[PDB]
Image (cartoon, coloured by chain):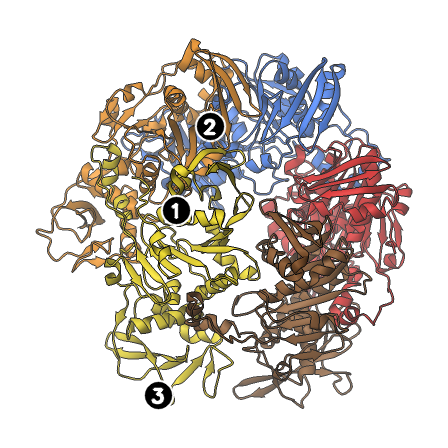
Chain colours: A brown, B red, C blue, D orange, E yellow
Amino acid sequence: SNEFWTPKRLLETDDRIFLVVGGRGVGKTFNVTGEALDDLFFNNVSMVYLRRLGVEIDELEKNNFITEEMLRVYFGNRFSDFNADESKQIMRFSIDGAIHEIKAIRNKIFFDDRCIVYFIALSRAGHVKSNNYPDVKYLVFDEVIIDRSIMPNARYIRNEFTVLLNLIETIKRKREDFYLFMLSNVGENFNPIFAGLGYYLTHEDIKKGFVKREDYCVQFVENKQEELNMTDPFVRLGAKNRDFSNSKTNAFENIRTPYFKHYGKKPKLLVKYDRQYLGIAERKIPSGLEYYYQVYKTLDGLENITVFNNNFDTLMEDEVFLEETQLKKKFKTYFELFQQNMVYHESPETFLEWSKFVYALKLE
Amino acid sequence: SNEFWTPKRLLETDDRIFLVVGGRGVGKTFNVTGEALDDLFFNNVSMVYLRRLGVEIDELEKNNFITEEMLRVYFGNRFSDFNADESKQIMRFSIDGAIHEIKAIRNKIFFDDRCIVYFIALSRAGHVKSNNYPDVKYLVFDEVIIDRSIMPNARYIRNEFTVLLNLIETIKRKREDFYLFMLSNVGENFNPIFAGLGYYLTHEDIKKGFVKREDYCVQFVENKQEELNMTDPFVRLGAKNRDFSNSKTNAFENIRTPYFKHYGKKPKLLVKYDRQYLGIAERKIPSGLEYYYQVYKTLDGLENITVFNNNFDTLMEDEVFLEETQLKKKFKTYFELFQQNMVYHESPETFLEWSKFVYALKLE
Amino acid sequence: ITKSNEFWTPKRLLETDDRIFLVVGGRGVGKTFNVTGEALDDLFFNNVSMVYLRRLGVEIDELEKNNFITEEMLRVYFGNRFSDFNADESKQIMRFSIDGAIHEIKAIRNKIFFDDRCIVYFIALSRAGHVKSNNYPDVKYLVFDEVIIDRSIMPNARYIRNEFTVLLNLIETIKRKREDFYLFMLSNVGENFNPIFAGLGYYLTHEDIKKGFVKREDYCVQFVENKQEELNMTDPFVRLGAKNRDFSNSKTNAFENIRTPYFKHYGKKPKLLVKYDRQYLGIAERKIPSGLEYYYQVYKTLDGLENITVFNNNFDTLMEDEVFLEETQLKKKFKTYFELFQQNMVYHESPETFLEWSKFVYALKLE
Amino acid sequence: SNEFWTPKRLLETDDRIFLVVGGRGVGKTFNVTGEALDDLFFNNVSMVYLRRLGVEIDELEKNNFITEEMLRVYFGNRFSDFNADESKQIMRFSIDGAIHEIKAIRNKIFFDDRCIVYFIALSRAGHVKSNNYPDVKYLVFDEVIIDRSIMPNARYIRNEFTVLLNLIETIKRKREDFYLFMLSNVGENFNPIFAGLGYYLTHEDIKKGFVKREDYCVQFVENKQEELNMTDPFVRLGAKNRDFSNSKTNAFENIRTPYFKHYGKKPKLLVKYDRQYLGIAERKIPSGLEYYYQVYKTLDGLENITVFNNNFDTLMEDEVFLEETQLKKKFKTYFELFQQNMVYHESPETFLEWSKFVYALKLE
Amino acid sequence: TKSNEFWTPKRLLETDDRIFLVVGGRGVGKTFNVTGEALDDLFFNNVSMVYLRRLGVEIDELEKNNFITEEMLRVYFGNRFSDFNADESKQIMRFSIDGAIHEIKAIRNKIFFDDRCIVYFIALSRAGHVKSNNYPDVKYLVFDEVIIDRSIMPNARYIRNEFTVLLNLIETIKRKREDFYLFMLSNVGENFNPIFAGLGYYLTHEDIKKGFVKREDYCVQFVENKQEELNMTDPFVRLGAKNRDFSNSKTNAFENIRTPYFKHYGKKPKLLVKYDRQYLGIAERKIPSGLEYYYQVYKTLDGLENITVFNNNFDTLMEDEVFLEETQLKKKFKTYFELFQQNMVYHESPETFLEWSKFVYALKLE
């Protein structure tokens, strides 16, 4: 729970959006909260612990989010005179000789009667748009990428990245000093979070520990068994199970790398999205078909190809309206062919544009 | 600073029924509740927060309905000595030197041990027809128009507007001083609320902020194209995603405007409704048929055309009784052809009469 | 909002010597309100209790109990006598003064108490089978509200299987050798083809409605008609409602359609017989080119109908050649006939026989 | 005032398991509790009121289980000074000049702060496995037999009689002074309770009031003497309804009497159960088949007939293991043919053997 | 009959092993006595316990106020225990130990001792949702009814990849701790389950006749209810004796252990899957009646050059091996897994049987 990773190396740089992939995950969330204690206690700022699904918060132990050892390791000699009423979910401790009290109730934690941690779930985000979060400096999004191994039939929230963005706007209103931590235990492409960030995961970027971008940073953290305690029976038992053993280093086991190929012929359909036109080209082969997902900056040269439009406002003239029932009829297989890695992309740059488009309109 | 829109301009006018469409939506509900606090506290009146579906009430946290920050902007200097016991679901504070207590338990909110807000759902209203709500001056109907995007499956209540009217009568019993607020974050036609009000949504009425009527007022609020701080990473991140950006202006993205056309031939069938006769005319074309939805003031000229009657009491011996099985046999397809915009209406005036009728008798 | 005629009161019914009252029509809030109000005096000071009965348990759970007895209620039925009212709504406690004595009304766990004495029980007809051994010591008032299903409000709401027999069992349990007992059945709509009317043996007819009151040996029936003569057209809510016919029709929809059956006599003998209530009910089918037309008949004795099949609901009374009407044999041979009854598709000999058939159908009907 | 049935005639005999069939049901539980009050109050013993389903206990009014007018008939002039707070579920009264208090909370009743009645449901027996019942002398099982007329679709607990035995063992731990009252409003065969007791209901035993067996007694009671008053409108209303009226005496309307016939031919299959052999023989008739359910104590004479075994542990040699799916494949129809009275049994003695076997393995 | 409290983990806590699998018995006594022997530590050594059940349904319906009972306190503290009084309204037990007053209250699926959490009630089916949860001082982890008894509930499935889920939970509860004990209690013992496969334990009647089986990583103890002579003068005892089902139910723990069939087949396999530094193979032998299947294990690919090889793991994927994604396995392994759970196939030996168990329960779907 006190791993070698710390967010100090990230807080010192000038960036404010961090994507941390890899690690125990149990240690990551623990150390992020600990490094934030000082600000939360004495700088009049709060924290928001965000999970995707409300079920993930109800089962979360709040009383144990801030724990005795958490304070001992992050305050040391400053800390003494600790007593707590776990039944009533209260802590009584002293820092620098001053007496403080932390109470945990419902989805909030208070420090001297000031909320310092909010527990809210993205699937319930529509409820929390009420701006009761005046001074939130840290937003922590934990387990932000689904591990298909852990939970095969798990779905992201509909239009998740827009929901998340709406929530940031609500939590952070005209605040310069705001930080967002996106903690993931596994790294892979083909998910709305990566697409929203516009990040394409590549082993070259993983071999390098750090990746800097205009709007955010990405940090990859390595786990290594190093020395194993083969005197402990529980440790020995785990070594005998391959599946459990691999789970320790399963972060980058399979990054989802698409296939890339170019096709000269013109596309069969076009859809206008983000002041561009996405295109799908089909090439007939004896076995069946080959799909090419393309991007065109202008309609010059592809005069009489049909153009679908998601938005009614940007609709015009010869474009056909993209209603939700007409879209399910025409794009379901194309989305399936995409989510399953069955198509050729022009380049990683086009792949991200298609990812944004797919995850915006995908239906569930 | 403070939100541009205010309900003061509406409370000053002589109308008592307000339909506010567009915006973030919480700011609407947030600001309406705040302006009412004064009456709720000192003039012995209560409030009712109405949602369509019981699910919309259960997931709502009643403690965040009235919040400190809300009390801050709506009382300024009169409010101080605020203390809150989240453990007991209590808020304590001092106003004008008087100490008050706000408690939320059993889906109710109290002020000095007097209920000031009731949370009840329209889908359960038929059972509580005998239930009473002694001193309610404000009725707030939130999210009164379904945003099909936000929710996968959401249905209006069968005969919703009549259920709503029935609830109004129960809540408001011979009170000359009563107010009704209907808040919508998205505006579109083909819904029972607009049909009940007899309002036809048009882009022309949106360019104008306000629309006065005899029985109610409609005010449209659009988000204000604020300057974006592109130095902020979060703002740049949002700018790179069009779905999130488009969501800011999706309130009036697509109002459902039907098609209008006249047909000289006589109708196939007639139904007597509201001292008038609604008619459907079918015109044969090579491709198939095209439908015309008409209204006739009198039977002059239409002698032997069949006439359906919803009401047994007003029935005549040559009219056919419109029982729940006979209308499924004959009018179900016409209702689908209506809900989907595949028919021609004589005019918006007749469209609203057909809308009222459809939403009155249509089934699921 | 405003309906232009006086509200209903049980004063005219308590004056007569009868004890079973069926009140049909009205808004409904005023009825239950005034029934409770007229009973408060007894409930408070004569050591008797009340039972508010609903068909479905959800109708009771969804009920707001603390608002059942309200400030303005005690004010109209005690007037000057009432004073010093203050209440802690959060704790569901009413404290008030009557004739200078301080009383306290508390509502907890689906009960209402007056000075620490239960005066109202909220019990649901659908849970009555579980309350066999329950004890209700001093109950003088039993109120059965919304006793007739309104097909408009509730699309596919169903009566309880053998409902009227369930209700009688509840009356006996609540009423244990008590001369002084009252039962109020209140309905917002009046129509035939329901177990309550069938159990009472009452046949609703417009003839009976023009007349306000009906006196029967075991009960009285009173009809109340809303009169929307004068309207406050200054109020927008009134105008908003007036422009919507559906809401407007709903105000007077109580007697919109009483379910009036068809009556016809057919001389030929029946296709089957069933022994019920010391009689023989018969169904006769007459062939017509379009199909068939059904006649539901009543026979006092088998003279003339020797070899016609006879179903018997009761195993004990079963004799010789009669066929026992067990629940699977009844589904095969009476499901369609019961459907034919509930839908108004058959000819009855007379209103007298129709009620005899109603008792039978709702007694054995299945769901 | 005095109810006519009493358990005194049963407590004086040397037996300890009593099955009382018939009556209102209200008087039975009322009178059993009354005869037990003395022991419950002054001999430091408790009672357990058992119902099949938790639904039957939650809806039960506990405070009214012991009532004032019950204390008067079973204590008379000694009972006095009665005062009760129904709101707080307290009864305070005097017996022999001593002040006592009865308090009812949740699902327990106390006498002078000593639990005298436990209300527990057979469907929750797994929850009470922890033995908190030191001094329980009375166990009362009410409405122990399903009345198919009152409740058509009501089910017994899976392997109910074994569950009951497990509960008896938990409540009674080697205690010798223990009494069990099984009270039923209906008498009929083909139920797990009768099968467990090994009692076969016969009109011959009903004409006789009492029946005495090694492990239990059965007493059949007809309904109280008092003839109904026709001065009361409610009585006439009930008198005019056939179903309600017969329902008063429907206890022995249809005891399910099986058919008995002997068949000389040997069985088609055998199943070993309880060191016995149950067999089913099929006799061909032109119309179809005739089934004979027989019992064989030894395989002498039926050498090469198959033998199914429910239990793997007792399995030997040529017997075939009876998995739960293979038995549903082969014994399901035979069980259906049994529960419906479609088969011939050698005798009532063998009928009970099949009842035990069927109800032991019968499935939902 | 009484509790049957003969069984205790005291003789087990003295041995050096820390993982105990106790199978068979009344079921109440197992959980009852484990909790009782641990009470002393829970009250006075500032450590807590975690009561683990497979399905959330088993905990919600569970009554927490009965977990620690009056009898338990007296039996594991004796005359050292006194002045017991309880408040049913609040469900608070107040008792005295050594003259000291303590109070046990249970709220929010937790039990507290002097306002300190001593027992957590958490369900394995929800453990995946909160991997990051903290449980500060847990010394005991008790997994009750860890083997599904098809009798207790007709329809019930093990969790997908359960043993990996459990280990992750073990790791979460036990951080920075060497003194930790894990109790797995089962009321029925049978093969073909993920817990046994994870432990690598193969149940055999030889191991049952002996009460105890010491293994390197865990201990297994089999408990048999003690034959208390029946009082055949008591009517209730006779009534129970006449119901074979009630009587047999007491000794039903090891009624049918699922023993697989073992046979060797000389031909080469049809398919191979690389798992745990080895190669699992399936060979089909044609017989007149139909087919008979052989589940094999090969230490090396020497000799089976052009046979197909599936690989669950992408990182180690090579050359001609085909990726075993969750949809590709349904097309080719669904029937073989069904044929495995039903004992319709031949295994080389119990050692290989467990390797297939690990593999099947790791990739099996529900």
Q: Quadrant of residue D138?
A: top left
Q: Are marks 3 and 2 on the same chain?
A: no
Picture residue at 52% right of the left edge, 57% below the top? E126
On what subunit does the disc labeled 1 rest? E
For the N terminus of chain E, which image quadrant?
top left
Q: Is residue D110 left or right of residue B213?
A: left
Residue type highlighted by circle 2:
Ile
Residue highlighted by disc 1: E32
Q: Secondary structure at mark 1?
A: helix
Residue highlighted by disc 3: E304
x and y percentages locating residue C72 in the rendered image: 74, 24
The label shown at residue E257 is: none
Is E32 located above or below residue E333 in the figure? above
Q: CA distance from mark 3 to mark 1?
A: 54 Å
Characterize the local packing of mark 2: few (<14), some (14-19) or many (20 or more) Cα atoms within 10 angstroms.
Answer: many
Q: CA distance from mark 1 to mark 2?
A: 27 Å
Is D121 located above or below residue E167 in the figure? above
The label shown at residue D109 is: 2
Q: Quadrant of residue A332?
A: bottom right
Q: Secondary structure at mark 3?
A: loop
x and y percentages locating residue B187 in the rendered image: 78, 56
For the C terminus of chain E, which image quadrant?
bottom left
Residue type highlighted by circle 3:
Leu
On what subunit does the disc labeled 2 rest? D
Q: Is residue C194 visible?
A: yes
On what subunit does the disc labeled 3 rest? E
Characterize the local packing of mark 1: few (<14), some (14-19) or many (20 or more) Cα atoms within 10 angstroms.
Answer: some
Residue pushed farthest left? D301
